[PDB]
Length: 126
Length: 126
Image (cartoon, rainbow over all chains, first blue to last red):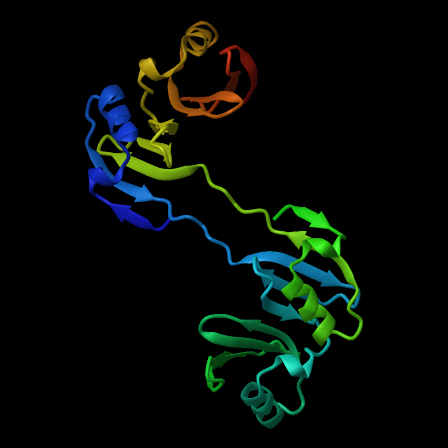
């Protein structure tokens, strides 16, 4: 529900005929086209150790939330793993999310860090 | 995002292998399947007389909101039209919505009335 247009040709013939038939002043002052809300996440799995994992329709993981415990080290990319072990040695990674931009990790002290696809740092927030 | 299951066979093979590979205690305590959010409304049209109309992907109207003015009488089913002219003669219909259950109308005094497909009264709220 983001695109807006003033072009009446965009609107289906049945809709245009409906407006012209039932409304006296039938001047269309813009049309909002509801873009289909396409969700990437289809599955959400809760484990017995209370850790939650989100997967897309093909079973590829998207988010791994280990709540207040540590994310298995094998899941965290080496440059990300090494950045945290250097700049935050007092802390552990509790949540990792992967997307098209890269990877976003969350620490035990609620610091969030964003890394790109190549694995180098981008930004963070306190 | 409504269905929940304890059946691991529901979850894709790639997701199941991911859990078994990276997690030591990999007991899946239920899976939430995100049911696809299928929206019936695709178009929303604003007219110059400030009245708003919502249509499905095929151009069939779903809602006609004439804000504080009257809905064109030709749009309101005759049994609905006659019910209002009888029980609410001091009032006018400002909004009409059609669905699978029937029709839901809104009056100028914010009373909402619900009618079935056959056109007879069902309920209302002050």
